[PDB]
Image (tube, rainbow, N blue to C red):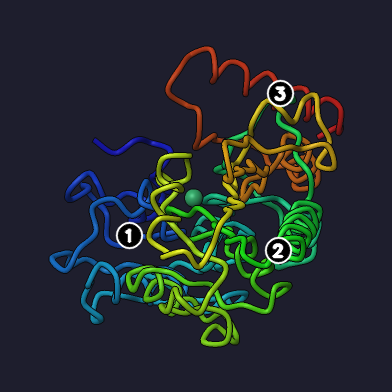
Amino acid sequence: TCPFYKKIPGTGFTVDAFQYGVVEGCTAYFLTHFHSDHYAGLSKHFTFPVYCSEITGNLLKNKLHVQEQYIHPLPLDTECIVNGVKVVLLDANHCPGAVMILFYLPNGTVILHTGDFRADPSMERSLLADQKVHMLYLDTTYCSPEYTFPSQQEVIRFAINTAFEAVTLNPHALVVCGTYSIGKEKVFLAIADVLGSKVGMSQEKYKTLQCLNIPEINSLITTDMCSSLVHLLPMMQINFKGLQSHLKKCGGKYNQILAFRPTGWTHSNKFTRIADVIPQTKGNISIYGIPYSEHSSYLEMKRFVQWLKPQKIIPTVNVGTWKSRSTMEKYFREWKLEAGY
Ligand code: NI
């Protein structure tokens, strides 16, 4: 049955709640983004109204076959009315199409649900700056001080420089990038752009990417693997066996693989700077794990909350153990005492 932290009090709404069958009293289902742990349950047989971004709505129609009459895409940064309640969608700085949702309840309460987000100071100048928020439903994925990671910009610099060096030393090396969901597209697109190649991929992944409004996508991606020296493969195939196999399939076009696994976090971060990262190597295959995150670090999360000063925080992640919950609640109290709210 539906957990309380997916339910918006004083409305008929739910958020990211499609795996519970018909939720009692739900008149509209919102979807923050197209990741399977959040859309799980949607299909062509869903007949309740779904509210979401334009990009998310493209993906629902084309990938899951949800019928068009039930998809209600909303523009960003725009006050809209849903079943008599004012809502706004804000950019979540997560994956393409991912939003945060502001709800303005009829009794004066204002609620922000972050969905999945990577907090950024740019958010301190959206429609959030303009009123008080009473309740924050917060993506607490990395809510512990050990989770530090570099900016996305520093991680993409490292990846472009590494790949450009490798292919310039050996014009017969192939670059491979792992993927399993939308998100982290900058990794493979920035590498392709520095090498003057398109990114080659399966027809299914190409279709997914064409749903995203990314300018000049026909320009950067392709299904013709032969013509490309940057290949996208499932994340599961990013190991020595999977990559030796792929290299066999390229018919002696290539004699080395440099592969990237963009992970969220790995405990290498506590002891290492980005500059100091090294691959795992076997034979003519090297694998780099790079800390490209689409969730807030601990310090990013803390800053956002100390700026917003909500009255009540409801975590949405790590809520299944008493130790995790207690840890998070202790950090929330620290933040509030330090900031004076
Ligand atoms: Ni997500």
Location of the N terminus (image quadrant): top left
Marks 1/2: CA distance? 48 Å
Mark 3 Cα-neighbour bin, 10 Å: few <14, some 14–19, many ≥20: some
Q: Is mark 3 within 8 Å of ligand 1?
A: no
Instruction: Select label 1 or label 2 by which is in front.
Output: 2
**Residue at (48%, 62%) from the top-left corner?**
232
Q: Mark 2 or 3 closer to N-term? A: 2
Residue 186, by quadrant, is bottom right
Q: Mark 1 or 2 closer to N-term? A: 1
Q: Disc 3 marks which amino acid?
A: Tyr
Q: Which residue is mark 1?
A: 29
Badge number at residue 167: 2
Query: Residue 317: x and y, percent?
Result: 50, 34
Closer-to-camera residue (222/265):
222
Closer-to-camera residue (206/41):
206
Marks 2/3: CA distance? 46 Å
Closer-to-camera residue (133/338):
338
Location of the C terminus (image quadrant): top right
Marks 1/3: CA distance? 31 Å
Residue 30, by quadrant, is bottom left
**Residue at (58%, 54%) from the top-left corner?**
256
